[PDB]
Structures are given as structure tokens and as C-alpha cells.
Length: 285
Ligand SMILES: Cn1c(=O)[nH]c(=O)c2c1nc(Cc1nc3cc(NC(=O)CC[C@@H](N)C(=O)O)ccc3[nH]1)n2Cc1ccccc1
Ligand SMILES: [Fe+3]
Image (cartoon, rainbow, N blue to C red; front, side, top):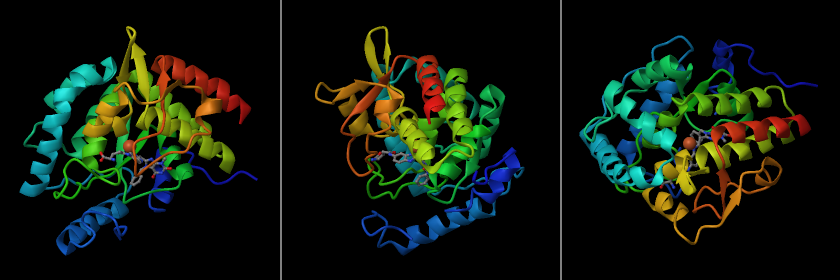
């Protein structure tokens, strides 16, 4: 039989909450950071569709961490990011307050995206099942972290944080072709088999999180996981990295690495082409 799936955007209230630092977390021994993280998780747990996303007063330390990462990544984007990223990034600086000394609010970003592509943000406490996470995309909802990485290492995070969301994900959700591509991953997942959902999540991971694209003959980055990580952003376009064409039947067999660089990156020819390839693929699963 078919598992429950959301039929309208407010139904995400029933799965957005179906989500403690792991031993190796840089804030693992810090009580104050631990408290701040509980503060953020509660905001997400108490959020209901229709609410304005609670605005957060970020600490001076949190803003410095953002500024440090932001400054270095922006040096690299012109020569590393795909053109769609570069086109949208300045609109966000203008309308959502992206600055070295200011962390943008998820509510302003959500309002900006609703205008551009109908995408919206939902604060999320932590990891959801792939079924639940992808189901949000069906309604152009991106489940998004609101907390900031620990200040001890601004250049590394073992998990998505809001720097990753804002710098890695948001500029492409503002792009119509990318937004369509993403939504169709969500739509395909609704009520799909467990196997199909895992395959869709892996395709998502190697496009939305770690995808490369070819533009005017050059390899560029569009994956959010690359766009928010200085070392892997550089590595991915280095001579050494193993690169293959995006092909869902093959890509979906690849393991998704969390604690290390990826072993392989997949190149999409364009968002339109990736979208077409997923359409062909979803027919088979
Ligand atoms: C597939 N899926 C799923 O099934 N359920 C979800 O809940 C889910 C999800 N995918 C996401 C979004 C996501 N972005 C990621 C980005 C990375 N990697 C990086 O950012 C590399 C950065 C780092 N090494 C650095 O130092 O910069 C790893 C995992 C990620 N998951 N999420 C949301 C989410 C929210 C909190 C924790 C985990 C996942
Ligand atoms: Fe991500």
C-alpha cells in the first residue's frame, strides 16, 4: 500500500517535526552552544505553516563566523560558481541583507524566494527521513537549518548549518529552472516506494548538494555543499577530482559521503537537461 504523503503545503506540519550533538561535533563539550542549539531546535519544532519564520538576534560571535566564511567564499564564486548562482547572489545581497557583518533572516529570504519562484523556507530542527525532506520540495518548501556552526572552526561543519543554507542553497532556489528541477524531485517522491525515495535522495545529493555543471566548456559548481565549503569548492574544480556525467541510473548507486570530500562528482549539462533525465528516470522506478 501507499505510505502517507502530504497533499497540501500545511500538511508538512505532520512530518516536518519527525526528526544532542554527536561525539565528534566541535561544540560537543560546550554547554552554552548546546543551549543555543536547543533554542534553535525549539523554534523549528514550534513553527507551523502560515507562521512568519521567527527572527533571530544572532550573537556577535555568530556573525563573525558567518563573516569569516562569507568573505572567503565570495573570493572564489566568480571563478568557481555556475552562472545562475552568480546571477542571483547579488539580488539577495540587495533584498535580503547578505553582508559580511549581517546574517540574513530566513523570513526575508523566504519572502524573496516566494516572489521569484514560489519557493519558501521552513525552519527544521535537524535531519528528517528522505521521504519527509523530499516531500517538502513537492510544495516548493525547503527545510532549512537556522543555527550557526560552532565558532571554533568557521571553515568546517559536520552538518548543514544556516551558512550552508543561505550561501549554498538559496541563490539557486531563486532560479526558475533550478526550482522546477528541485520541485519535480519532491513530486516524484510523493507516495513512492522506499527504494524509489532513496534513489531520488541520492540523485538530489549529487545535483542539489554536490552537482557540477558545464558552461561554455568550463566546469562550474552548483551543489550547495560545494558552494559553502572553501576546501571542497576548490578541490572539486582541481585537476584530481573524479568527474562523471550525471546519469540517474548510475548516479543513484553512488554512496553519499558526509565526513569526507566526495569520491566522485557528477556533471549536469544544464538544469533543463538534469530535469529531463530525472523525468526519464522516474518513469522506471
Ligand atoms: C537528503 N536529506 C534527507 O534525506 N533528509 C534531510 O533532512 C536532509 C537531506 N538533505 C538535507 C540537506 C543537506 N545538506 C547537506 C550538506 C552536506 N555537506 C556539506 O554542507 C559539506 C560542508 C562541510 N564539510 C564544510 O565543512 O563546509 C551534507 C549533508 C547535507 N544535507 N537535509 C536536511 C538536513 C538538516 C539537518 C541535518 C541534516 C540534514
Ligand atoms: Fe544542503
